[PDB]
Amino acid sequence: SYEIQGSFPLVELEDLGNKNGLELVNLCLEEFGAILFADNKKLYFYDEKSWYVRTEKQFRYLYNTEEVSVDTNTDNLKTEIKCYGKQKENADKLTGDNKYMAVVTYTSPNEAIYGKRMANAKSDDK
Amino acid sequence: MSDLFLELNGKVHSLSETFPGLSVQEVSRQSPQLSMETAEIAGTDGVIPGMTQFKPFIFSAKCNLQALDIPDYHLAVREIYEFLFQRDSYYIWSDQMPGIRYEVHPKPVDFSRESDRVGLLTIEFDVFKGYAESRGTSLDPMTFEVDLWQMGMNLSNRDDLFYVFRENTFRVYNAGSDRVNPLMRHELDIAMTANGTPTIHNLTTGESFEYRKELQKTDVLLLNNIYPLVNNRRVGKDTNHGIITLEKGWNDFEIKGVTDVTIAFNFPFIYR
């Protein structure tokens, strides 16, 4: 049995089905951004707001912690991206970005701290 | 006079009686090996103790062998080696404290040949349970003719100690130095016969064992260690899987849901 506790957006999907229960549950978690916790055979699906509960317990250095480690990676630090929408019917007859009705370049504000770091273009044809 | 008694295969053998040429000079017992599970946090002082535990220790007996002649000496040495070293652990106790026994395994000890017919020995038995236990269980009566109880076994000289009860609320006295817990590989048996659906509560410890079926007076409920049975049939699925424990000293027990209760406790005392 399943229970839902929270608010989630609508997601458009193609030919849903032909999968086991766990695959569909993982798909739900990845798409709707839910968090799954199971009371034995009863699966509760929360959102970020209703999952975490604030507590007065705290982690203090030299008091109840021994080794603290932070791993930081900046191999994928990108602040600019170019994306293309669907493809026009007269794609062969057209040239350049005119092949797509939707072409947009997004630049994050964090560029002001890191400069322009543009990544490989991603294409969504839907 | 000192002597050492060995319980092996259900038979009690006196070391001096079995080997006439061998006499026990002295016995001794290593102190309990206390060990706190320390946890260290770098930058702070000292350690954070966990739960104190007790490591296995050594019971030693200094003795000598006096033989008639050299072939007799060699034969006696071989026979002593055959007798002491067995496949499985056995029990030992001493004349000095004949009410406390240890489950032990022998250790390699070499004869020290001093003359052509005399040899000194210092037998060492490793006791691995980490504790000593009484020779008799709680079911044995506290009577003189039983010849089992001695002084220094923490017997309360202020009130009677019985381990069979006929009412729904009583007190049971654990005289040992450790809390009797079957989860710690301790020996503990409860035999209760009554009518109805039973529930046993140890108030001092705060534990509760619950059985969820009707019981008749003819059926005996036996909890041995961590196994509950009725008529020697496992019924763990029909219980709450709780287990009771006996704290040091007095434990207040209350039984609910049944009438004409007859409950008996059978466990040995844990010393150290």
Image (cartoon, coloured by chain):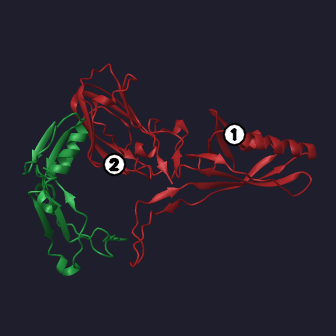
Residue in the picture at 40% in, 23% down: B232
Going by the image, does B179 lie left or right of B90? left
Find out whether the residues at labels 1 and 2 contact each other: C-beta distance under 8 Å. Answer: no
Q: Earlier in the sequence, mark 1 or mark 2?
A: 1
**What is the quadrant of residue B88 in the picture?**
top right
Residue furthest out toward the front: A93
**What residue is shown at x 28% (from left), y 29% (from top)?**
B238
Which of the pair B167/A126 is nearer the observer?
A126
Which one is in front in this view, the residue at disc 1 or the one at disc 2? 1
Q: Is residue B1 above or below residue B36?
A: above
* Left or right: A44 in relation to B194: left
Q: Position of residue B191 (x, y in %)?
A: 37, 30
Q: Residue at x 50, y 57 (%)?
A: B54
Label 2 secondary element: strand
Q: Position of residue A32 (x, y in %)?
A: 14, 50
Chain B shade in the render: red
**Residue type marked 1:** Gln
Quarter-of-image position of residue B13: top right
Colour green, chain: A
Please provide percent x and percent y for residue B266.
42, 36
Q: Whole-Å distance between the Cαs marked 1 and 2?
A: 39 Å
Between B208 and B66, the one lying in front of the other is B208
Q: Is residue B191 above or below residue A73?
A: above
What chain is tagged by disc 2?
Answer: B
Q: Which residue is mark 1?
A: B86
Q: Which residue is mark 2?
A: B250
Check disc 2 and give the amino acid type.
Trp
Quarter of the image holding residue A15? top left
A115 vs A96: above or below = below
